[PDB]
Image (cartoon, rainbow, N blue to C red; front, side):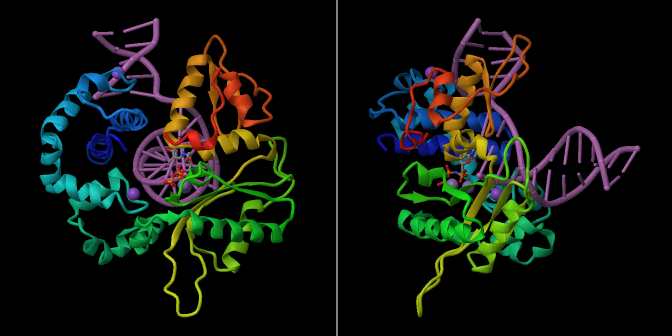
Length: 326
DNA sequence: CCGACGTCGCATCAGC
DNA sequence: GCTGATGCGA
DNA sequence: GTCGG
Ligand SMILES: Cc1cn([C@H]2C[C@H](O)[C@@H](COP(=O)(O)NP(=O)(O)OP(=O)(O)O)O2)c(=O)[nH]c1=O
Ligand SMILES: [Mn+2]
Ligand SMILES: [Mn+2]
Ligand code: NA
Ligand code: NA
């Protein structure tokens, strides 16, 4: 964090554009800029120096010069003072509440945590659970707790069917010392790109984790993706652990490497890699890498038998999970 | 100058 | 009910 | 907001 002040500024600007202006490409522009500055191994001395980096243009360069000279940004100082922007930004911190619902709530005079708590009937299920655990979801997860959680998940999954493979991805697989949540990739030989020989594969696992009181709430749930809440068990007279967000994704077993590449992240890393893939004439999702034809249409899936194969196709040197934290 | 910006799952809604 | 778009999220 | 062509 040689340039923590700058990256903080840009992230706050990113959040404004996403939540208030509802301009998603500005949000990504700022986040991309923040990321490239974050890994820049010098303390930045000027906006001109920063503009040399890919993703930093004229406007951000000027903001960096203002921030360097004064320690502040007048544009952000004004935004911070605005009631509507501040209220909208706050409401979006609740899981299930996005830019649209936040602005609608503020219109209806619901703009504080207290306002939300007395208008619970106006929330959908996701938002209601998000409000319930607002405090808990603010807290990060120490890696040591992540290891406890991994142990439970992998063992409970094993008990259902010993041919399941569960892999913890996201920031954990990238070796982070603390995570925002837990991300679990799931495979079973019955579910491939060719066929589904077994129903309720994800359901079976979710059910087991509920039975042992690990999973406590559900935000969303379908055939391949689960979004919910979990909690570590605590001992006698111990204060309870905070409730944690958990994401589970069932991927066709023969498409594990594309799946694990996707869910390992980071989000910005995926954006950068897939953009580069397009430049190289391929498209990548969580299932396949495919060539783009002359007319621009995706062709048939290419052979993949390691994460590295995917890097090879787009002419990138392989990068370990710990080097993908962009 | 300006088109494009990664890709997709689940909840919810409009229109039929 | 289905189809397609919108919102929020991974 | 940025940038490749
Ligand atoms: C949010 C997001 C996530 N992903 C993939 C890559 C992420 O690393 C992976 C898990 O999402 P996450 O749990 O929201 N983020 P994280 O695990 O990287 O970091 P954190 O510690 O959970 O905050 O899902 C995307 O591909 N695009 C996205 O926009
Ligand atoms: Mn995560
Ligand atoms: Mn997650
Ligand atoms: Na630049
Ligand atoms: Na939210």
